[PDB]
Each structure stands twice: as structure tokens, then as C-alpha cells.
Image (cartoon, rainbow, N blue to C red; front, side, top):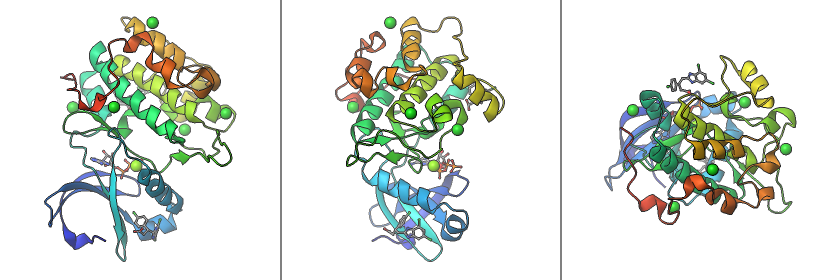
Length: 284
Ligand SMILES: Nc1ncnc2c1ncn2[C@@H]1O[C@H](COP(=O)(O)OP(=O)(O)OP(=O)(O)O)[C@@H](O)[C@H]1O
Ligand SMILES: O=C(O)C[C@@H](Cc1nc2cc(Cl)cc(Cl)c2[nH]1)c1ccc(Cl)cc1
Ligand SMILES: O=C(O)C[C@H](Cc1nc2cc(Cl)cc(Cl)c2[nH]1)c1ccc(Cl)cc1
Ligand SMILES: [Cl-]
Ligand SMILES: [Cl-]
Ligand SMILES: [Cl-]
Ligand SMILES: [Cl-]
Ligand SMILES: [Cl-]
Ligand SMILES: [Mg+2]
């Protein structure tokens, strides 16, 4: 079991509402980690215990190159510590903001990596539920590292669970089924995927308004459109993901899963095997 004094801490990488992620070097190995640190007092007082336990449980199940890895956990009197892989190039969102619109090849490359990651996650019976560019980090080689699993859900194989009842997510990316039936499912992540593809090309996600309530209203009416020059194969894919009926989204279980999704013409050029070993196109 590791201890705080086993590390030298460097710069703060980011701060959440109830967490702080700091860059750290382990003295005995010289390895770098992003260590996420939570104050026990704050977690208890503010009803966050279930989210911390959830995050640990979900991440412990993950063993795929496109996800942040949880290497170890420890605690002292005041704090809990998650030792995570360090994604040196930060959030995908920052690149979307800087560049405004990814070209087709960069759009396809990152879409493909997200699809690959979702194939794995859903194959393990896990829903992310808060997929968004802020939660898609980038490692030193510019491959994705998906993060933020405190609001993910492990669906129970014992009961053949398909639906989850917790209300979680981010307004711009939240699915219509969560807003109207008050449940999410694997296909809810595919809705978010469609929002993300759209945003890579269009700069802003599809359902656009200045507060959460206005966005909710647009989502349930499928109120959005495409800017000019939106790559046609990408547009077709988005239209097959942003479908109000969650059982009709390309990639969902009722549509026979990821095979048909990976077969979409948008991914014609993609070699899905060893995707994480391919050199990524330059953003930038
Ligand atoms: N493994 C990592 N490598 C590099 N940076 C990270 C890593 N994990 C998190 N960060 C950065 O630290 C910031 C805070 O992450 P954390 O999950 O602790 O809180 P959050 O989810 O951003 O905040 P909130 O809880 O309010 O949603 C993130 O915005 C991210 O940019
Ligand atoms: O396996 C371990 O190392 C201990 C566990 C158990 C654990 N102890 C806790 C104390 C508090 Cl105050 C809150 C939570 Cl969510 C707690 N979870 C633990 C440690 C660290 C982290 Cl980040 C999560 C869970
Ligand atoms: O999507 C983000 O959260 C990143 C930011 C800020 C931003 N996000 C928005 C989402 C919506 Cl729905 C609407 C507006 Cl006006 C929004 N402004 C942003 C601004 C400009 C550009 Cl080109 C890209 C991203
Ligand atoms: Cl940037
Ligand atoms: Cl929401
Ligand atoms: Cl549902
Ligand atoms: Cl097409
Ligand atoms: Cl892969
Ligand atoms: Mg988080």
C-alpha cells in the first residue's frame, strides 16, 4: 500500500467541485501519475460517498488503452487518493475551442477511437452517462483517454439490467430518454457520441442554448440542424445516432450492436484492430 510521502507532488492539473488532480512522481520508481485527491470531510458532508465508491468500482474493472487507468488507491486521516494514468495533453474540449472545426480525417480518427472505447465499455455492461469532450483526455501520443466514471453505471448481468434510474450527465449531451422516461441505457452513450461527432465539425454541440432548461426543451424535440459543408458521411452518421427512439440508434443492442456501426461508410478507411498503435493525424 502506497502513502502520500511516497510521492513528490508537482503542479495541479485541475480542480473539480469536490476533488483536486495533481501531477506526481513516485520516488521509488520515478513514474508519473495524475493523483486525484478528495477531502474526506467534504465527501461525507456533501453526500459524495456513493460517487467515490462508484468511481473506484467502475475504474477497477477497466483494462483498455482508451481509458484512464486506475493503478492504486490509498488514504490518510484527511484524504482519499486515486492514482491514475497521466494524460499529458489534457481535455479534447480545449482543442475544439482552439481550432473550431476538425477536418474529416481528424474527426474520423477521434470518432473511431471513441466508438472503439464504447464498444469495449458496453461489452462489459457499463454505461458512461456523461460522455463529453471535457471527459475525453489525450495522452502524450494524442490517443484518447476517457475519464470521469463516478457517474458511470455497472448494469447487472444477474437481472439482465438494461436501464438505470440515476439522473446524471451534462445538459448539452444528455439523452432524450433520460429527460422523458427518466432512465438511461447503453444507447444513451450513443446519443452523446452523435453530439460529439457533430461538435468536432461544427465547433458547438447540436442542441444550443444558454442554460440547461432551454437545452432540455430542444433535445426532446430533436431541434437542431447542420451547418454548411458538414462532411456528408459524417452527417449521415450523426442522423443515425441522434434519434429520439433509443432502440433505433446505430450501434445500440436492438440494432444489433457495434458491427453495423463500425461498418458505416464514414469509417470505410478505418482499420479497427490495433487502433491504439496507429499514429494519430495532427490536429494543428
Ligand atoms: N488522468 C488525468 N490526467 C490529466 N489530467 C486530468 C486527469 N484526470 C483529471 N484531470 C484534470 O483534472 C480536472 C478535474 O478532474 P476531476 O475528475 O477531479 O473533477 P471534474 O470531474 O473535472 O470536476 P466535477 O467533479 O466538478 O465535474 C479535469 O478537468 C481534468 O482536466
Ligand atoms: O481500498 C481502500 O484503499 C480504502 C477504500 C475505502 C474507503 N474509505 C473511505 C473513507 C471515506 Cl471518509 C469516504 C470513502 Cl468514499 C471511503 N472509501 C478507498 C480508499 C481510497 C479511495 Cl480514493 C476510495 C476507497
Ligand atoms: O462546448 C463547450 O463547452 C466549449 C466552448 C464554449 C461553449 N460551449 C457551448 C455550448 C452550447 Cl450548446 C452553446 C454555446 Cl453558445 C457554447 N459555448 C466553445 C466555444 C467556442 C468553440 Cl468554436 C468551441 C467550444
Ligand atoms: Cl490547444
Ligand atoms: Cl442533465
Ligand atoms: Cl428508456
Ligand atoms: Cl453515408
Ligand atoms: Cl483498439
Ligand atoms: Mg470527474
